[PDB]
Image 1 (cartoon, rainbow, N blue to C red):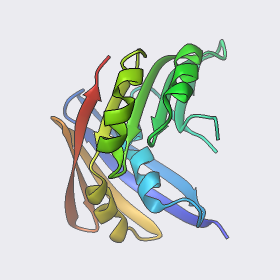
Image 2: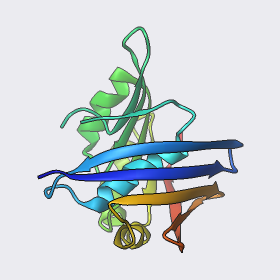
Image 3: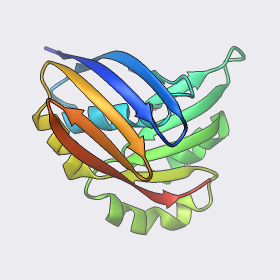
Image 4: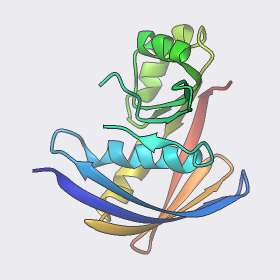
Length: 171
């Protein structure tokens, strides 16, 4: 059965001067891991002004469809293949990649040349910090996300965890 998570988030983006309170309800399946779910939320927190939306595997993780049905923003969470981002870069105006695993530095060392031939941004999350936030996640968890510099400070059940955002490719 799908595990139901409810997140009450108080957001503070001190880089873009954006403050909002988002309530999100996410469904989790034993196949998917809670670490990838949190990485999608952090990308939503980093790009909340884009009015993104979560998705239900070729479909992106987060996107914003305009009235012309043109994908304005494409947010992929994970370590995708360059051919996938190659297709996504044509369909979407802006494509941003957020990796969240420990294999990312080795993955980037092999995909650096191909991704340099794409007008996208590649940024990395600290996995162990995301794993930490997972351990203190209740079925219904009240989170507080603070964004400053190149790091994300998350308050989850009084526990404070810093998640660094390393830049691999700008745009």
